[PDB]
Amino acid sequence: AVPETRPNHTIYINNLNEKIKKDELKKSLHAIFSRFGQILDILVSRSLKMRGQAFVIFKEVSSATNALRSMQGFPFYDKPMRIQYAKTDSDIIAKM
RNA sequence: AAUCCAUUGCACGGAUU
Image 1 (cartoon, rainbow, N blue to C red):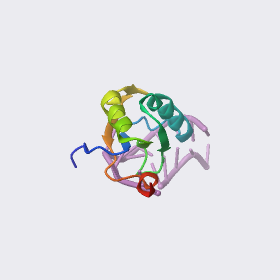
Image 2 (cartoon, rainbow, N blue to C red):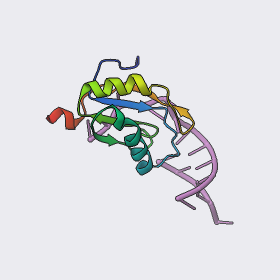
Image 3 (tube, chains in turn orange, cyan):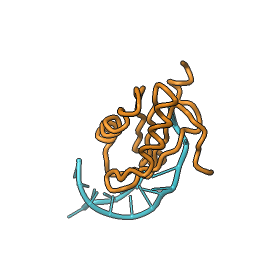
Image 4 (cartoon, rainbow, N blue to C red):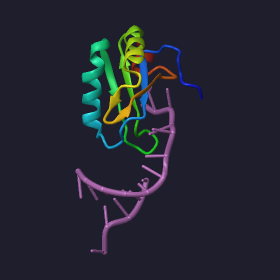
């Protein structure tokens, strides 16, 4: 699957250092992405399938787009962040 | 908790008398 480049309120981040625990990762992600707009939530799972990944849900698509373009490749816990838009809407967004 | 193995994965595993 080619990188998902169609704008979405949610950015999908992968290539994250898997040693960072869930609480610290969410807190560090919030601290860094909050300069782009209002974050609705950050979904992190350390399961086999979902580890090394995170979903940052912005209240506005414009915030997600700026976040993606700006933070693409940022060296984080010694690995360049890889960012795409989520393929589908987050449920929080989908109810709104 | 820690170390190790395996995992690059689009959601809402495994090992350490």
